[PDB]
Length: 94
Image (cartoon, rainbow, N blue to C red; front, side, top):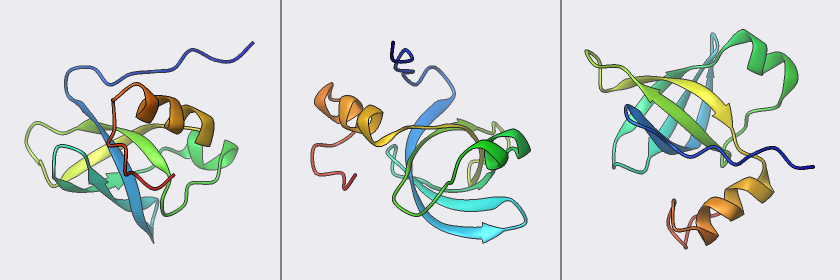
């Protein structure tokens, strides 16, 4: 069946991809109100497309809050599940 829906934990935030920057980076608007310039991991890049509007789980960096690391990308269905469960705002464009 379907993979378990991963929720954010301490030191992580949900985000929505704003734009791709290349050199394996993207700008994400995170739902704690912070824009973060995020590293995309090689393994992820190979298996999935990451595009503007995608919902992502972001690992924070203690010393650089303007930066982060993409742990995972949510599928559209998973993103709607997050919304239905109140994890991201109801008005988020999926």
